[PDB]
Amino acid sequence: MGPSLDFALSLLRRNVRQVQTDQGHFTMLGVRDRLAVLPRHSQPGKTIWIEHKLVNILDAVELVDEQGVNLELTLITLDTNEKFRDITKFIPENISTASDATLVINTEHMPSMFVPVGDVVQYGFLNLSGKPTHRTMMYNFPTKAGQCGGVVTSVGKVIGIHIGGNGRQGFCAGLKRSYFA
Ligand SMILES: */C(=C/C(=O)OCC)[C@H](C[C@@H]1CCNC1=O)NC(=O)[C@H](Cc1ccccc1)NC(=O)C(=O)NCCC1CC1
């Protein structure tokens, strides 16, 4: 087996989890230690179902930029025995574009799902259900409901979390390493 498939499968195995909040089904990315990240609109409460058990959330942090504008990411710290494999070195120090990215989804409804979203470009501002959002990127792929949390990735790099779409395009919140330091 080759490098790109091996990397995405290993991600699925170690870092990308099936979860459910009161808002329904999402893909969650575990980054290091007890720190994971979800799309903000998933509204994780005091607990979150992770794969096969209800896990308690010790802390949630909604990321805003310097303007106080929503970045549509929530850092959660879990009460678990698990330490996630540390993947912070796969996340670029700044929000980076990519060519021929793959969206990795892992939901009860869409388990271990690989979606070739193609090239990923800077987008910046995006208006989501009346919520304005910054630092987004775009891919021209008709992404759909149930795919939020999905992990945008390419050549051993983890560059975004899927958050939205318009029926023709999809959009992710971009990752940078400092969010997880
Ligand atoms: C993922 C969440 C989900 O499935 O829950 C039910 C909504 C979902 C994926 C996109 C839906 C349609 N196609 C997709 O790829 N995202 C959303 O539903 C988000 C929710 C959101 C995000 C930020 C703040 C508040 C809510 N919203 C949208 O996709 C959206 O509101 N509008 C699409 C058009 C606007 C981008 C121009």
Image (cartoon, rainbow, N blue to C red):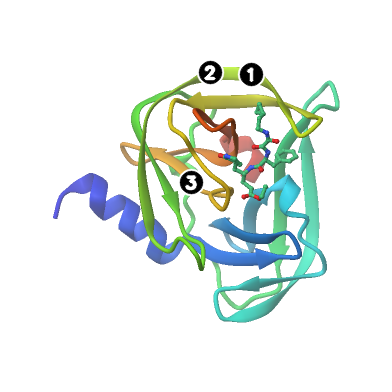
Residue 95 visible in the snapshot = no
Q: Can you give x and y, in whole percent of width and height, for residue 119 in the image?
A: 37, 24
Answer yes or no: do the residues labelled 1 and 2 have beta carbons within 8 Å? Answer: yes
Marks 3 and 2, how far apart in space? 16 Å
Q: Residue lying furthest right in this view?
A: 68
Q: Quadrant of the C terminus?
A: top right
Q: Residue lying furthest left in this view?
A: 1
Marks 1 and 2, how far apart in space? 6 Å
Badge 3: residue crowd in 10 Å (few <14, some 14–19, many ≥20): many
Residue type at tag 1: Gly
Badge 1 element: strand
Residue drawn at (66%, 73%) of the image: 49
Task: Judge whether 73 appears above or below 93 on screen.
Answer: below
Residue nearest the viewer, comparing 3 with 115: 115
Left/right of residue 60 with respect to residue 176 in the rendered view: right
Answer yes or no: do the residues labelled 3 and 2 have beta carbons within 8 Å? Answer: no
Q: Which mark is residue 83?
A: none
Left/right of residue 43 with respect to residue 11 in the rendered view: right
* Mark 3 lies on residue: 151
Residue nearest the viewer, comparing 129 with 105: 129
Residue drawn at (60%, 57%) of the image: 26
Q: Which mark is residue 122?
A: 2
* Mark 1 lies on residue: 124
Residue type at tag 3: Val
Q: Can you give x and y, in whole percent of width and height, for residue 46 in the image?
A: 82, 69
